[PDB]
Image: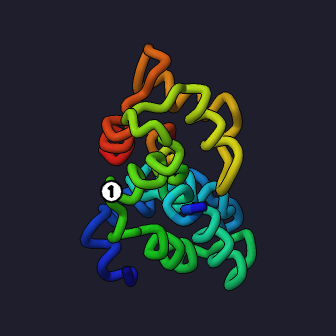
Amino acid sequence: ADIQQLEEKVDESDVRIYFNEKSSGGKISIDNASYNARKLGLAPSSIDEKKIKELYGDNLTYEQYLEYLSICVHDKDNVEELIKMFAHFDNNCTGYLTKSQMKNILTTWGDALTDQEAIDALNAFSSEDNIDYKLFCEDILQ
Amino acid sequence: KNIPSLLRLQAHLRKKMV
């Protein structure tokens, strides 16, 4: 995604308003840029954050913030890759993982969530201890 | 293993919680 594509997917008015909400001295921190990206429905990972940081440092001008948002687009995202990641841990091929198991996965590798973030993400999907991870991934991409 | 896909999942969880 370049900025032109980005501004067909998100509303530029929101992009600007959210920048104004968080900016200081005409610039926005990467943490606040990621917060804005999420509000706009985008899903940055640490890969995207480290990329923009290498280019511009941790405090972005408006145009650099636009370039960051374009990096956050991720058109190739899909449910299948997520299900397959969880299915890796589903040895008995039940289609289920417990909340404890999913919490472990989410808080151990990659851009690890805190225990509370993981608990809150899981409890929000289901009151029950056994999670149909296929249904969970469909819901997370909703 | 499968780290890229895990990062995408964690990214969507952070998105949804925002």
Q: Residues within 10 Å of mark 1 (few under 14, many from 20)?
A: few
The coloring applied to the image is rainbow
Return the x and y of residue A59 as percentages of the image width and height.
71, 70
Q: Which residue occupies the extreme left position in the image?
A: A8
In this orientation, which residue lies closer to the viewer: A47 or A131? A131
Report whether residue A19 is seen.
no
Q: Locate residue A22 relative to residue A129 in the image: left or right.
A: right
Closer to us: A48 or A93 = A93
Q: Position of residue A25 (x, y in %)?
A: 70, 65
Chain at tag 1: A
From the viewer's perspective, tell me whether residue A95 is left or right of residue A50: left
Which percent across, then down, holds residue A120? Answer: 56, 27
The extreme top residue here reads: A127
Q: Amino acid at mark 1?
A: Glu
Location of residue A73 by image quarter: bottom left
Q: Which residue is drawn at the image coordinates 62% and 43% (left, top)? A: A105
The C terminus of chain A lies in which quarter of the figure? top left
Residue A113 spot, x, y in % from top left: 65, 42
Q: Does residue A115 sit above or below B1 in this rendering?
A: above
Name the image quarter holding residue A31.
bottom right
Query: In the structure shown, which secondary structural element does the residue marked by tag 1 occupy?
Result: helix
Residue corresponding to mark 1:
A80
A70 left or right of A135 in image: right
The part of the image, by quadrant, that contains residue A54 is bottom right
State the quadrant of the N terminus of chain A. Answer: bottom left
Residue found at x 68% / y 85%: A55
| Number of marks | 1
- Who's the residue at 52% across and 61% down the image? A44
Does residue A83 show up? yes
Q: Is residue A1 left or right of residue A57?
A: left
